[PDB]
Length: 54
Length: 54
Image (cartoon, rainbow over all chains, first blue to last red):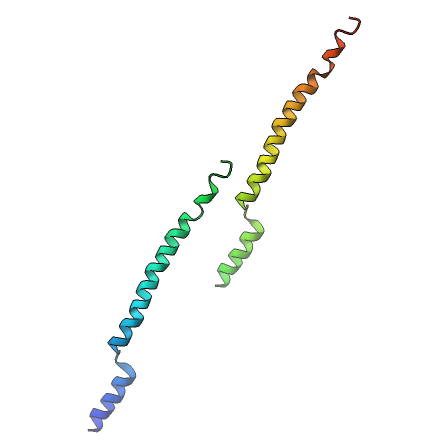
């Protein structure tokens, strides 16, 4: 019984809650795609220079 | 973060804003064509000598 409770206690401190962590995984997965999108747009975003009298 | 903000800083001090310099290049390019055209006519200036009791 003390083993079952201190297993439960340690599992609370250290095992991943996979439900919760897939929220935080997937925020960062969308943000990474939106970041790569913005970087890919930003590298095109200075093609504006080339019409200016050139 | 600091390296981005001092790249932003130094870029402000040192990089040509190509929009602003293509104004000043084009002023001087038109002035040079105008001043060439003006020097060409200023060399025809004293052609008036040759009809003058000659």
